[PDB]
Amino acid sequence: ASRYLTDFEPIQCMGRGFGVVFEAKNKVDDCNYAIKRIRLPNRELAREKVMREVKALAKLEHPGIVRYFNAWLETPPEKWQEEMDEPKVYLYIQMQLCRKENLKDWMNRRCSLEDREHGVCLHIFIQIAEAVEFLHSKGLMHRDLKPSNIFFTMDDVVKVGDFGLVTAMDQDTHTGQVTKLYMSPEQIHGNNYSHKVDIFSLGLILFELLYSFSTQMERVRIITDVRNLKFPLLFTQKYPQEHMMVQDMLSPSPTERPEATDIIENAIFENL
């Protein structure tokens, strides 16, 4: 008997990191969770790598980090028939139910400057930074940081929440090809890299937060140039300090990119 259905009533699908996620209600505690389900790879090395996410989420407690509840495995007969309605190992991981629309959706709903309040943009950035600071302090790397992996709770609390590519460090060879725009140059050409990769993508997000995009074609165009340190005049002008901060975060030399705690300590961050 399938544990997922035994303990939960699926309420609605909600999309895709690698696998699929549903809103499901727990039959005994009677409230709603997000159930990420991953079709598991073979030969127990690829699996162990997929397992990293649950190993990390269970030892992570931070107000800017998605609340973990449970993780189990299922080896069912003919889920295939069951799925089309909604050697076959599935990883179920039970999360806190966040808001439906993530940061990427939040930004699409705000395509002009006047929507993107300077105060709010920093407030939601800092929480990500703090979360990354914690994540780094416990010797871990996200290596996938993009608005679509940042979420909001019902209390409007920003939480970074897709650790499908989380891994550990040492005194800071890893895997090379590991998200399009947000991937750091080190990974791009194939090199030895560090947690400093998270600071790179963190920089891009801060630009994205402050610079409102209109089309995916525009978005790609400007983001590509911002990676090469070419900045729109409208950004260079009204956000000079942020512009200084971002370019530091975006330098091709990993050691020149600030530490997470450095970025948080910056004057720019004020008061509620």
Image (tube, rainbow, N blue to C red):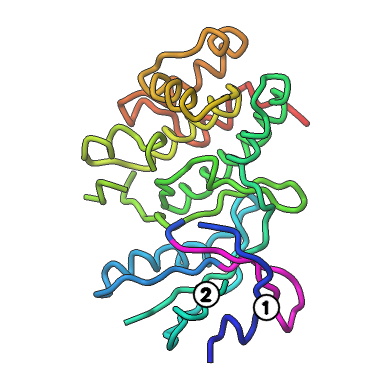
The numbered mark, 2 or 1, whose residue comes first in the sequence reads 1
On the image, numbered disc 1 is attached to which residue? Answer: 9
Query: Closer to the camera, 113 or 124?
Result: 113
Residue at 76%, 77% in the rendered image: 30
Using the rendered view, name the quadrant where residue 91 is placed: bottom left
- Label 2 SS: strand
Instruction: Tell which tag, 2 or 1, sits nearer the viewer.
Output: 1
Indicate the amino acid at tag 2.
Ala
Residue at 51%, 74% in the rendered image: 83
> Vertical placement of 260 versus 175: above or below?
above
Residue that extends furthest to the bottom in the rendered view of this protein:
1
Mark 1 Cα-neighbour bin, 10 Å: few <14, some 14–19, many ≥20: some
Residue 173 falls within the magenta-colored stretch: no
Classify the position of the C terminus by image quarter.
top right
Residue at 67%, 48% in the rendered image: 152
Residue at 45%, 63% in the rendered image: 19
The region drawn magenta spans 19-35
Percent coordinates x, y for residue 147 in the rendering: 54, 40
Residue 31 falls within the magenta-colored stretch: yes
Callouts 2 and 1 close, C-beta under 8 Å:
no
- Label 1 SS: strand
The numbered dot on residue 71 is 2
Percent coordinates x, y for residue 95 in the rendering: 60, 65
Query: Closer to the camera, 134 or 200?
Result: 200
> Vertical placement of 56 versus 190: above or below?
below
Percent coordinates x, y for residue 81 in the rendering: 48, 80
> Which secondary structure is most common in the magenta stretch?
strand
Image position of 236 (left or right of 34) = left
Using the rendered view, name the quadrant where residue 248 is placed: top left
